[PDB]
Length: 284
Ligand SMILES: [Zn+2]
Image 1 (tube, protein in one colour):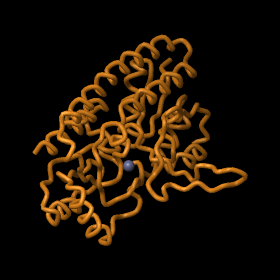
Image 2 (cartoon, protein in one colour):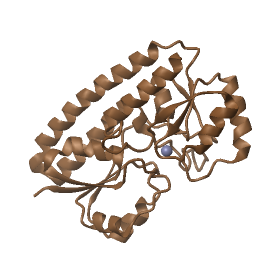
Image 3 (tube, protein in one colour):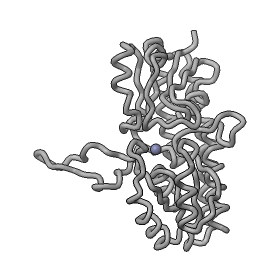
């Protein structure tokens, strides 16, 4: 019978649907245009995990509710951390932390969790999906591994596509500003710097003491355009676009897919909506 699979949010939900095919029954907890940083599960989510065979998660404390939800669900499921094997980036500030015991240990934690904004990282996510499906359903492993290997092929072409478009840009204009500091893996991969009022997580609200400072950094970096994000309320970025004298060029997709009929209804559509929107604005 089909593998009962729950993914914590929409993007890895797309990775799951792509590897699992018709062999799985997906149930995503955090939906399109929704924010996992501040998500807080409904009793249905405990029921889903208790009824699940595999739980797919991002790890690095993206899902702050995860450990409490597993406990309330009493689930027996294999929990996959799709970050395993990704070469992960430190949070900014401060920056972030070590602390020696007998020796020096990378502290708590932070690790920037947005590893998916770099397509080579998304391949590791997909690797880790199939391994988690092979583990719970030996009979389908050859199918899982063949879907993942095919999708990883399309991911590789997406990467070539993205780097090629950013390389064609004048290097003097590589700075944009978004809602929260969610695109640092995009920068490490492809070379667009990102400014934002909010930090790595959206839990803390953006204060007025950030705007004058951010406006100054936007000028010193000659940032080219301001984007809203699909998971945040756009009003503060319109204000910043005004005071900075910069166009509000559109909406980027950070931590969630769009709905269907939307422009980022799957990951590969998502990365190309962003790369093209970023590309067009910097060329202007
Ligand atoms: Zn985020």
